[PDB]
Image 1: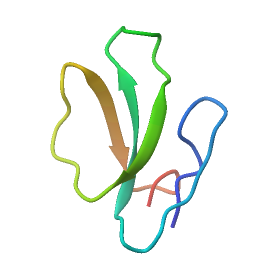
Image 2: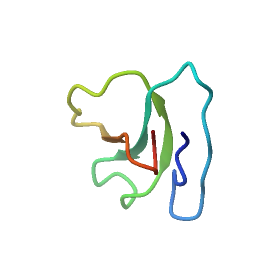
Image 3: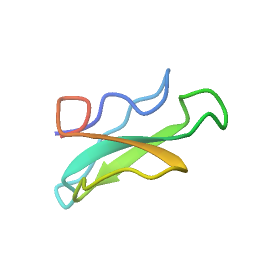
Image 4: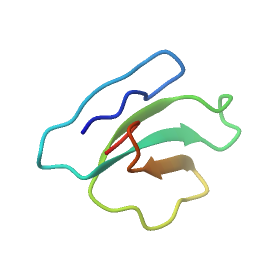
Length: 60
């Protein structure tokens, strides 16, 4: 599967060695949208980057 989104106008896929996907943003740093990538596990988030992890069609 792949992630059909990463930013407000971006999209990308992944290999078979990853697991899900997550759009990494900032906490009120810029605005909300920033970037995204693949993932292997999704525990919790942090107070520095918005780790929006998901395994839906927009990720896994």
